[PDB]
Image (cartoon, rainbow, N blue to C red):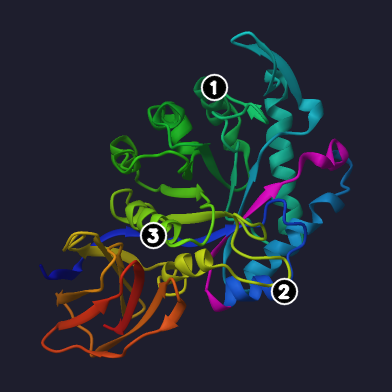
Amino acid sequence: SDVTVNLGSTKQEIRGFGASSAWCGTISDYVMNSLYGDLGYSILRLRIEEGIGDAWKTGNFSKWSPELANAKKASAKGAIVFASPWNPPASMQENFSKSGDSSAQRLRYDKYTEYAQYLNAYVKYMKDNGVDLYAISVQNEPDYAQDWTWWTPQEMLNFMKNNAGSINCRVMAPESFQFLKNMSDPILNDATALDNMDVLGCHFYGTSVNNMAYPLYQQKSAGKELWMTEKYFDDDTTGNIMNMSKEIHDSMVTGNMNAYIYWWITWPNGLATSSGTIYKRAYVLGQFAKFIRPGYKRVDATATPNTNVYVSAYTGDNKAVIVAINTGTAAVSQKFNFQNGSASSVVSYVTDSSRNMAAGANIAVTNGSFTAQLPAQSITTFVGNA
């Protein structure tokens, strides 16, 4: 069946695509130039380093300098930058007994004010150094915390109502490890908390496709954004290339998300080595990042035109973008039809077992239509002038 791309019917606005510099120390220009320049990543996620301890109170920020350097490289390439904490400084924590386990850690209730000042100090350090942070997160995975700081949904709510309004930046929350709605529902159902939330962040570890849709957020979404802020895939084998291609599609199409941000950069389950090698997974994300620029909008496109074929489409800057994934083991031809606009022609870029965002066949668009071969187990991005 044909794919109909309706350029006149717009869906969510695209904030961007990116990865994280968390625990990467100071990333090289080489790696940032490859990811942020060549592949056009538009978002970088910093980890806020609690190893600073209380020294933030006296203004010695040196332990925050590696992520400042990362932020500056991303920004120079036009990316925005946000930051997530795994823990506050040790002095703000306390143990508590979590179902018989006395080792669990949480933020002291009497520290919520100090913690907001801490978050504000990170924002200001970045600002004084030339990086205006796009958003800052209350906690990374407050609901899978055994190795970090726990927050119940109610604890997160309390901070979001009473504290988060004093933060000098956009506020992101909750970053549930699986996008568990019980973690974000209290924020969305409280008028004050909702006011204090700019970006609803979530992670994909174990999230089923149907659970990527969030009706309550959609009904509450005026003035807000929804980002998938962390996911990784194990390696570059074709199964994971397809798993990753398909999930980004699902985050865009079923999730209606504004952004999809990969986990950390120079690591084996990451996108690169520190000496500048770039993994196939980086190019999978680039099929999105490079061509769908911040400010583009998703538009309606027939999403599953054939077995194992998944398609989404986007417009902006007088360009049309179609991302077509074929998870099948055989190449298939796919016909595409533009409505409410058209393109003179398109160029393609393909990632598969042998190719990394490789230039594809230039294709003429006739009567608003073009047909393409989609290789077996491949993701292809077509770009044309609208």
- Type of amino acid at the residue the image marks with label 2: Asp
Crowd class of label 1 (few under 14; some 14 to 19; many from 20; radius 10 Å): few
The mark closer to the camera, 2 or 3, is 3
**As displayed, is residue 233 above or below residue 87?**
below
**As displayed, is residue 26 above or below residue 176?**
below
Residue 127, given in percent of the width and then of the height, sits at 71, 57
Q: In the rendered structure, which segment of residues is drawn in magenta?
A: 38-56
Q: Please state the total of marks drawn on the protein image.
A: 3
Residue drawn at x 63%, y 8% as measured from the top left: 100
Q: Earlier in the sequence, mark 3 or mark 1?
A: 1
Real-space CA distance between mark 2 and mark 1, rounded to the nearest whole angstrom: 40 Å
Is residue 250 magenta-colored?
A: no
- Type of amino acid at the residue the image marks with label 1: Thr
Residue 345 in the figure: left or right of residue 24: left
Q: Quadrant of residue 319?
A: bottom left
Q: Earlier in the sequence, mark 2 or mark 3?
A: 2
Give the structural element (helix, strand or loop) at label 1. loop
The residue to which callout 2 is attached is 29
Real-space CA distance between mark 2 and mark 3, rounded to the nearest whole angstrom: 29 Å
The residue to which callout 1 is attached is 152
Residue 220 in the figure: left or right of residue 21: left
- Residue 324 vs residue 190, the one in the foreground: 324
Residue drawn at x 77%, y 40% as measured from the top left: 50
The mark closer to the camera, 3 or 1, is 3
Q: Which mark is residue 278?
A: none
Residue 87 in the figure: left or right of residue 335: right
Q: Earlier in the sequence, mark 2 or mark 1?
A: 2
Q: Quadrant of the C terminus?
A: bottom left
Q: Quadrant of the N terminus?
A: bottom left
- Residue 168 vs residue 327, the one in the foreground: 327
- Type of amino acid at the residue the image marks with label 3: Met
